[PDB]
Amino acid sequence: SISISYSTTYSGWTVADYLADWSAYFGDVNHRPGQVVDGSNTGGFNPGPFDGSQYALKSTASDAAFIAGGDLHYTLFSNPSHTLWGKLDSIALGDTLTGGASSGGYALDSQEVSFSNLGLDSPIAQGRDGTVHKVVYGLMSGDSSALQGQIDALLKAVDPSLSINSTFDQLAAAGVAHATP
Image (tube, rainbow, N blue to C red; front, side, top):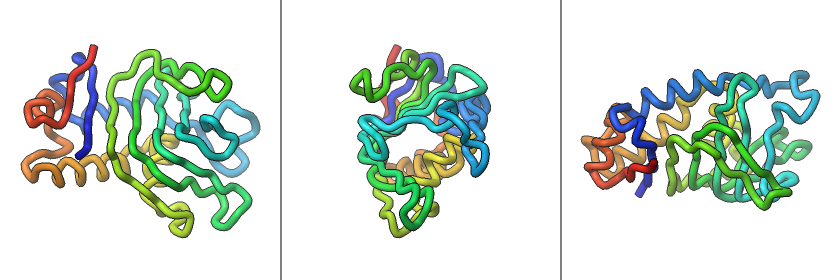
């Protein structure tokens, strides 16, 4: 079952509300052909170099950042090119990305919301159209709609009445979410 972890600030907020606001704050790191010319909009794997239990990225617009958790791979020059695939079990949305592979992992200084047991596994075969690639590149490029659709499917799987338009305190009442600072 999907497990959701949220800050007391966003008690009254719906999941869609928060995800839109967060996407707006993060914006778009412009990770596209010709537009990746240093390390500022690449993000990082832990441990890396091209696979890890974490892929992390901080906004080049703001202090907003996310960490993707599971067993993630990036193919680069192996068909299909520029594919991010493997197991995604969690996403953490927060400010002030700290650490990295040198530090033994990434952590959010100020985590706002987290979704865990996503149970997404996208094979290399599916290239860019695997759910894992759509979700992560969505958060990279300022569109949280893939993540939203997945969270909505999980929420409806646990209970039909639950929705992306349920508040965090409503989902907490329904046993799904647990409140944090």
